[PDB]
Amino acid sequence: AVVNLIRAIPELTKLLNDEDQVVVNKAAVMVHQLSKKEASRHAIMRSPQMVSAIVRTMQNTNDVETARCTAGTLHNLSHHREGLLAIFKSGGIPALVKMLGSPVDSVLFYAITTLHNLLLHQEGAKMAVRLAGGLQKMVALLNKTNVKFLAITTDCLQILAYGNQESKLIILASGGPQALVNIMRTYTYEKLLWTTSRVLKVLSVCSSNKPAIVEAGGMQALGLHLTDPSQRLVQNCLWTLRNLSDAATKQEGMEGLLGTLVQLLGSDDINVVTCAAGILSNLTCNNYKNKMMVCQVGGIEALVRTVLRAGDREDITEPAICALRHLTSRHQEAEMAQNAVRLHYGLPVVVKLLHPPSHWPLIKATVGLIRNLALCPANHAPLREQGAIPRLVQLLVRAHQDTQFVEGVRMEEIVEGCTGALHILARDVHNRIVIRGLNTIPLFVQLLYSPIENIQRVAAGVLCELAQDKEAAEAIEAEGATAPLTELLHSRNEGVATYAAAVLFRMS
Amino acid sequence: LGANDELISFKDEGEQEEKSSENSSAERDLADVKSSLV
Image 1 (cartoon, each protein chain N blue to C red):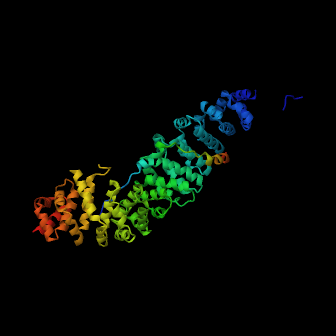
Image 2: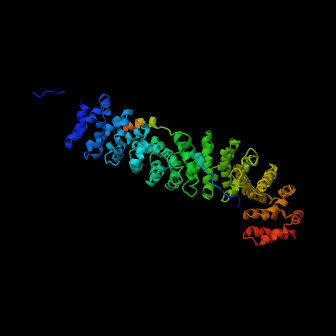
Image 3: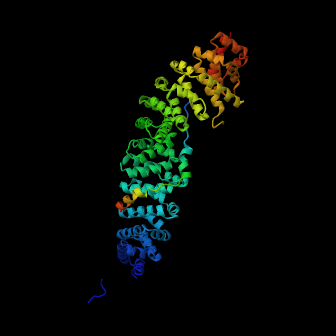
């Protein structure tokens, strides 16, 4: 009796447009079943009206099954360029972004996966997602707990944020840093850790996102994975940690991170060595706690070995030397550190670094390290024997000449640094003879006239030490040092005033 | 006592990639993840 049992697209498109929702729901199911077959797919993808109806129904329906079926249909069409284009041109992105707010998982999954496909292969998709407010929706979803979903969501964020300062700011405003750090500290799924580390790397170069990542516990979270078997993950964490380092010098609970970084200096991967050295240099800056920990785990030796391996590679020696500089001053184990640099055979290479081909940034740091090393009397003779004095004087003379930004460094800083190093080295009777013999007194007296308070201090300091010897005190007086030193008794700097009084007393 | 500590900026080092090189694709790793999630 009932016959005709077993143009389909044009018929279904009409049904999805029906005002009757029960009809729309049933048609939605049929369309979805058809999207499962490649044959029926092309027919759907080629119909502008079909796609538009699917997109409209999805964002307007109140039926969960209809939302699921239409979202699933679009996902099925997203595997082909033609499908991606049709979805794109039919207003699919705003619709999909709206679906990211759905309380049903199946719908969210179809939406985020289809969006990822659009972002990867559809020209114009990134901009559309940003405009539609996708960034904000995605960050909000980072509190979900399905690790596969989180991996796709975070990668979408990476695609959208890469090379786009505005997107990074949006992510920041939506609380992205804290959510991303939470992921790093909570999950173990490598692909997610990796996609998430890529986002953090991108954000870490933003001056606004850097402080937010650090305060969220980012340094500690990234540090937790520096030993994971995934090389790509370790590298991403290291690069990110380095970018953030200059903003994490006030963080606590860095013990674990510092320990691993020191061990990483012993890596055969020069890129890992370079990053770890850079991170260590910044983390040891004005933080006695961090210096203590680094020294306790053999950091001095590791850093000396790093300098030796680096050779003339200044992208490795600068941070390694700066780090050694930080480790040799102002902390309970600074004295031990000053001795360790010597006991680990580092005095010769440190002095060598004062010579060409080293550039000013490295020389500046090296002078600073030698200044620290000189605080340890056992280093007085070794430093002299390696020729440190003559070179320091050479640098001083050159730098002073200029003062009468060079290669990125202010020569005034070199004058202050070399003269300070010489001031400390002059504590040694033998070094005083060498310093005196290089005809340095006239130059030291001239520095008393320096407009820089710190230069007058170290100049008076070295003259004070030199004046301990009669003949020297005589040479200092003959240079007309009396006049300026007397005026310096009125210095606002206690050190200057004190050193000046000491020299005046000795000249008499 | 001693030299003053100083920070090092890695601004250029970090901004290098996003300026000179195009962004990498993670499809190889996520393809299976996406099909599985769906």
